[PDB]
Amino acid sequence: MNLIENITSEYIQTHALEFSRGFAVLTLIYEQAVQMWKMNVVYTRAGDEEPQPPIYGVKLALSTTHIKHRNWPFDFTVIDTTNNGMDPYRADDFETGRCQLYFITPEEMIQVRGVDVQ
Amino acid sequence: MSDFLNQYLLYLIKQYYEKPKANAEAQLLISTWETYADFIANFGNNFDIDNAEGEVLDLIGRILDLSRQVNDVIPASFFTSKVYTDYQLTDTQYRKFLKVKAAKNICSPYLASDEKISLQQVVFDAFDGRAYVVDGKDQTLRLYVSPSIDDDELRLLINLDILPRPITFRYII
Amino acid sequence: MRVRTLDDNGDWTFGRGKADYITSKKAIAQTVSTRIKSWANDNPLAMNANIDWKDLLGRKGTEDTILREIERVVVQTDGVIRVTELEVIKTEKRVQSILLSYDTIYDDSE
Amino acid sequence: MRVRTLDDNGDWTFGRGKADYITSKKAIAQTVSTRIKSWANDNPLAMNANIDWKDLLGRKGTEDTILREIERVVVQTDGVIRVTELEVIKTEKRVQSILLSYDTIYDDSE
Amino acid sequence: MASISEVIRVSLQQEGRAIAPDNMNAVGIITGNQGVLSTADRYRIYRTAAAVASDFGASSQESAFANTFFDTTPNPISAGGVLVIGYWRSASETVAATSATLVSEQTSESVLIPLLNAINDGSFTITVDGGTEQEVTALDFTGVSELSEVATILNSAITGATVSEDNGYFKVTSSTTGATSLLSYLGVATSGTDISAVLGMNSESGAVLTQGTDQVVLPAETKLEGITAIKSEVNIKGAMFIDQILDADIPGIASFAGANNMLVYEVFDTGYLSKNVSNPVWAVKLAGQSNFRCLLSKSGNRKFAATYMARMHTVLFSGQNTAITMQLKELSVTAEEYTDTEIANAKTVGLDLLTTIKNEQALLTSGANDFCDNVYNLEAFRDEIQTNNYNLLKTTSTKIPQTDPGMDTIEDDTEKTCEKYVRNGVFAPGTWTRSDFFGDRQQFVDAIAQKGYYVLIGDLADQTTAERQSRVSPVIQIAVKNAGAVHEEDIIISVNL
Amino acid sequence: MSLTFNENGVQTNTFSELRALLEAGYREIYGTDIVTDQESPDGQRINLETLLRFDIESAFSWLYSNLDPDLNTGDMQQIIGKLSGLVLLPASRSQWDVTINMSRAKTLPAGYTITDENNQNWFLDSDVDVLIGDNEVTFLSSLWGSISGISGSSFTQATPEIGVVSISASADAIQGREEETPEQFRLRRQRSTENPAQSTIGSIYAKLAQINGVTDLQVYDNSSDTPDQITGSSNPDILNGSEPVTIGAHTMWVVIEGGSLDDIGEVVAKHRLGNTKGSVQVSYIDTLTKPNGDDFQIVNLHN
Amino acid sequence: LRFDIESAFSWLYSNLDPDLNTGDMQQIIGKLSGLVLLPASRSQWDVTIN
Amino acid sequence: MSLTFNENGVQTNTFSELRALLEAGYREIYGTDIVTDQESPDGQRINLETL
Amino acid sequence: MSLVNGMVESLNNTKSETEIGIGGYRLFARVRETVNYRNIVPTDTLEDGSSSTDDIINEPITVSIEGVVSNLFVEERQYPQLVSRDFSAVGEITALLPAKSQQQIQRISQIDSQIRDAVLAAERAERLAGKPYEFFGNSGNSAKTEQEKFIDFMEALYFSRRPTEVSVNFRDYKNMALVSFIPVRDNNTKDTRFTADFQQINYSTLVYTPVSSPSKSVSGKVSDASNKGGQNPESNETGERSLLSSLVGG
Amino acid sequence: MSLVNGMVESLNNTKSETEIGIGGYRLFARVRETVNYRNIVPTDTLEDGSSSTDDIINEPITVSIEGVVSNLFVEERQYPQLVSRDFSAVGEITALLPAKSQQQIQRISQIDSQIRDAVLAAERAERLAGKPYEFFGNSGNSAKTEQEKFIDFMEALYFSRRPTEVSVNFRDYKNMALVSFIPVRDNNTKDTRFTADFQQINYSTLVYTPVSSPSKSVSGKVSDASNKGGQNPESNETGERSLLSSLVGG
């Protein structure tokens, strides 16, 4: 687990996660009319050009695999730097460090699922 | 004039908050969107096993693998909304069976499991607090119940395996 | 530029689509007329919508800045060219009425 | 910012963790109150901790620099904005008492 | 344990700065509830909500009014002002029997102690309940470091009464209540160095000796004109009543507002949006009682006055153009909803409105009665010329001789005040529109048109010798023109079709 | 990109694209030079509509995501707890009994708050009447959590009421149960998924051996109904068991020496579920929460 | 616009049904128990090298 | 790197890392915005302990 | 480009009567006051004789103000500077947010009280972005004379590295950046004679924005999809927390 | 960056009453006294219209002081300059150090007396780093007139190549480096008219340091792991001592 740095309070931001088994595009969306942090990813395997079908609109929540069912070798779990285990809900909730998002390494999804994957 | 309508009308600039036609029209748009807002807010209220009737209950059944078809006959809960066949479940019974099924889905063979959820806690709040599980000798699972449940129901749950049961089970009267 | 006409009292108009729209030289008239009326920190979607009234009619000694801001709003309007505006009464009770005259982009075709 | 509360006489408080901590607007109050009290060349881990007292109350003609240094300490505090401070008595025996007033970052929410 | 504290101490401010209602912004709230302000405690001065609470409790409506007072963002204490709670006897105050008291002179504690520590032996003569004269012949004051200690010594010495010290005062109260005279002012004893005179308890000294009042006394039930008792004690410059002034008593207080150079704010409900004679507010407007400001609150929400008061008396009359109007200024109370007909009636009758536009307060003030701006500002001007003339007659060691240079002195001081209040934004130069003046009309109108104010003092030789040996200065006539503020805007678009 | 709800999730349409769509519409309906700015009626309403749809799309994504059992906040009590069989124990306010000493008889207001010495506000729930002397009355906390009400503190009043002379608590304050944190509720739901770390024979041995105070213990179980046989153990020597032994019918049996007795009972109730053979009886005590804020005691007795 | 949102509602409730889910929402409803779709597994192949 | 005493010797933990460890601790116990500076009681003791 | 834009945005800076000074510090005297409108007109004779115009590139206006600051400045006729309102909640739009239980609400309340202490300073700063004086504020201490106040305010503005608004008579330019501040103290006058050159930071909007300047309550709401660069999370050390114990099993 | 930093570290240099001069040499007269706050604002119109701010790069303040030095300067009203204390042993923390025998202790005493003679000069220098005057000291010799003292102190400061602290009225800037010192001697006045430009050496801390400025007794103790470059010891000649006779066998 490694910390995805550079997450600001602006509502709709994109971070291109470049890693070993291909790369993904983390679109962090902040719904304010109802406080949460949606996430979108388009993980393209390193072996090809057309990305796998995207995920769209999952919350960020504490201590939980987010994209596990889409069955590719990474996911994200956020944790709260307080002990108030409240899901990320403020716009600035990542810049101040109240909650922070962690990118799970594929080698660590190995320890999670117990088996490799595509 | 609820919260939604009021906070949205502030986006009417002040040339148009007071002209009756304009205010009425903006309220019309806000109201039509407000019924969706209310629907989203009340989805939680009206979806769960408690405040669910008819098809949603059946949906819950098919998500917890329990159809209203138990193929058995139970006497009526004579204390209209919906009627089924005799050999099906009136709503309230099928509700609280689905609660029991939801419990037994997350069972565990521990009466006070500190790490995972126990049998006792989940069977107890399955029955909303009118059940009590204590083990036996030949792996009997004695089960005390409040008198607010007829014998027919419980004997049916044991005769359909909806109560939480690792290997062996029983009841008490 | 088109814009929905407003009736005498200034409420909105629906129905007669493509016909409740002011065509021109009057669309400019309506648009200036109610650009003046747009308090600044009203609209959350335009917080500098137009001139700031709660902070200009509530403070002593702003008549010059009222006039400069009215000229700003009017001149920065799609369709006007010049202005010619000043104050005609002198707060007949305490309300001053100013006279505003502007040359639209029309009536300059000779 | 949290900080452990101190009781009336100013000794430390243990027990009631997460509850002996001052929340805010009072955490600033406590932190300024005892930032003033931090002699400079005291702490070997911060030798310019705060203003230098053994070299300002032991020398004649420092009242202006006492006041400037108190304003320095207060203003450079996480949570304060302004100050408004001066001297209220004139060394009633030889001790002068100064009055210090500051606007925390709170009470500016309108 | 020699603490750091004895080279520096840092504590929290304790007393409410203990200031007095000197400036214009000394506003009042009159209660009628005999909780803590009984008669002879007719007023208390505050500069924060919490203190009003601690003397009044967040439950009593008086603390509620203080809360809605201080909650106005530019509240009076932000411009050299105080709040003061008054007290009019609403119904049958029962003053509990007191005991005789003896408050001594204001002693600084820096001089009383050094004089005391040399006095080995003691010497008092006191009398309690008119009993046998008591003489105290041994008070080893040598070991005393603060007035609390001499207080304890006197407490042990004076039998039949208790001695306390309080803010440098020495109070001595007999135990018994009701006809309990402390005849003595600490008279001279037969032997021992006299402590009495140096303390301040002495009869020749300025020691208050309120005798023990008779047993329980009933003041009757006064009228709202009992505001006079507050006004004759506090120099309030703007007041309200918690309880609504009855219709039949409005003119009186209205007249009062003018006659005492103050403002009184009073709110009325919807039933008063007429212009008949029977409507009291219009009766005020016809009577010209411009100092009796009338406010309108549909619900009847009395607090609207306090915040309104708390919004007005808020101008430091020393900076430039600090004179503020009223309209469209944030208050501390929720606005109400009014129709257009009723808001027009309020405009044309004299009431004032805090009306919603959109969740956003809009204060609209009338000009039927003179604008609150004008009345308040004119009151400030009369108060300030009074203060400046008083300060001139006070400053000089000589007597300000009754010669023409003296009148030029006084006229120059008045002109300085007028210039301040023109720089202050209240009066501005303009063409004097009225049809009356003092001296040369050309001189008068030119001075108004170019400076904004005119100050003419009649010469000495134009007053009777009856008014010459009365040591009274000649009549000083000053004329001013209000600045031309704006409240609405009727922008007229020049039509070219 | 715009709102699409597919096998891929719910792509929510952003504000700028949404308003541009509505503006392109209005252009198509009325004319290419319609003025749609802050002033114009069409402008006002295009702005109102685009805001309304942006917010409703946000609320719809709220719905979609909070139907996810592994990601939910406020209907998390609702969508899963009553659907997967859990309960979120409602929080409580810590009741405190306090003697308030009172001079003048009064009705202390609905919600006046006193504050104990650690900046914690205890508000009286409803209006009370206090008599001439000492009054035992119950304040409820303002923090809904567990609020440690030490006995014997000094209280200063946040909302002073005239007359109090002495606020003092003779005894401490019974705490208020705090909720399972949303993180902790989700984690408790999730832990039911993964397999146990040990086999059921070895589960007890593993989690009965960290009992602080033991140094050795062994377990002999009788899985098969054969009463006095042995079908497993923690001792490798028992593969044949060349001696007779008395062990109950389809039971499991543990011997420890030097163990925290109550801790031993707790662990056995934590992992046994059945009949335990032994001589000394030891129990766990657990609290079970009826839906109303009560406490039902359960004793799990093993041997 | 409004019917876009309402048909989203209809689709949402249509996908609270294990017998009709057919997509990501199927797995979201599938997390309601601790099971997810099995992942693709590389095929094993035992050989003799020398 | 921090204090480890192994078949390799005794790696002694440096000051900055040690105080950062103690500070991360106090953040975990109490709250992420605890003020730990020269004045604050917690700051005083974190410094004392790390020293 | 267009000739129409000239008058339109020439009036876009209207000087309020209150006469902000170097940003609210008007307590000096303006000995001289200049602005420098410059232009780059490419030199060589333009190519076509029909349409090859549109070749007057604009320039950043500079504004030079030299004045003097004394211990005692008496200002003649200028209205008070009043604190600008906190119009942040103008569009604040709650009541669509979820229903969540008590001490689930209050947990959010504690988080809000917990990071408001860390954000509200910069929030006020952005609220008061143009005008630094009422941000830094009147010094308020009786020890510091007026030249104290001018120097410490100027240093605060200079170290602030944030653009300020500067008023020459008839214009209150909105984003001036302090370019040069030279205070001089002759040995024949106790005052301070200071020359300050500011340079406007003019910046236009490249991208489609329907809303010019919204509230803070919708400023992020109407923001377009912002972009951050890539990064290799697998190769981070500063936060390489282990896998949560709740995940290794699952 | 932040607007908050402005006032915070604008007051970070407070002028003491004692009025250090060019570093403690106040025995001249300040004919003129200027500071030059400069800034680099990148010119072209900034890119976005939403957030592309934070583009006012700061600059090294220069301070110019021109004055005159005469044989006889009479200073009007200024407090004495008192020698700063040697607060080095404030945290000095012994008594954990080992128990070692006499003349094992005293051998250390001789080593300490042996290299204190070689380090204490630079130790005092760093103790008196900002202020060179009381390091160099009052000249003390009656032969050298006052202009002697000013010239030799200025040359000592200039050749010292160490930054000094310079006080303009209302500020005692902490690290000024002597940039230019021009003394002039007209043939119609025996005094010396000197212009000295200093430039601040502003330098911030890149790395995590919990302690701002500790004692000498813990300054190395809290230091982070310092880094020196590599080197090839096998290829050194200046110290190629043979192998000790006690090692060849062993």
Image (cartoon, coloured by chain):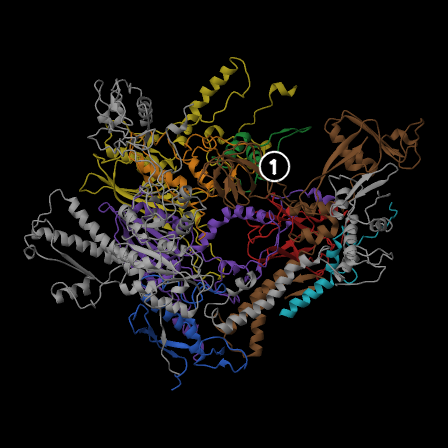
Chain colours: A red, C blue, D orange, F brown, G cyan, H green, I purple, J yellow
For disc 1, the marked residue is F174
Decide: is H10 above or below J28.
above
Point out the image quarter for the C terminus of chain A.
bottom right
In which image quadrant can residue E40 be found?
top left
Viewer-proximal residue, C29 or E293?
E293
Residue B94 appears in the figure: yes
- Give the crowd class for mark 1: few <14, some 14-19, many >=20 residues within 10 Å: some
* Left or right, F209 with reference to H44: right
Query: Which residue is more in the foreground, I130 or D22?
Result: D22
Question: x, y percentage for residue I225?
Answer: 58, 61
Quadrant assignment, res J67: top left
Q: Nearer the viewer, residue B44 or J128?
A: B44
Give the secondary structure at mark 1: loop
Please give left or right for residue F2 compared with residue B138 in the image: left
Measured from the top left, where is residue F236 in percent x and y? Answer: 87, 30
**Is E424 above or below relative to F299?**
below
- Seen from this angle, which residue lies furthest bottom? C110
Q: Quadrant of residue H6?
A: top right
Three-letter residue code for mark 1 = Ile
Where residue C48 sits: x, y (%)? 44, 64
Q: In the rendered image of this protein, does residue A52 appear above or below residue E188? A: below
Task: Name the chain letter of the residue that bears numbered label 1.
Answer: F
Residue furthest to the top in view is J102
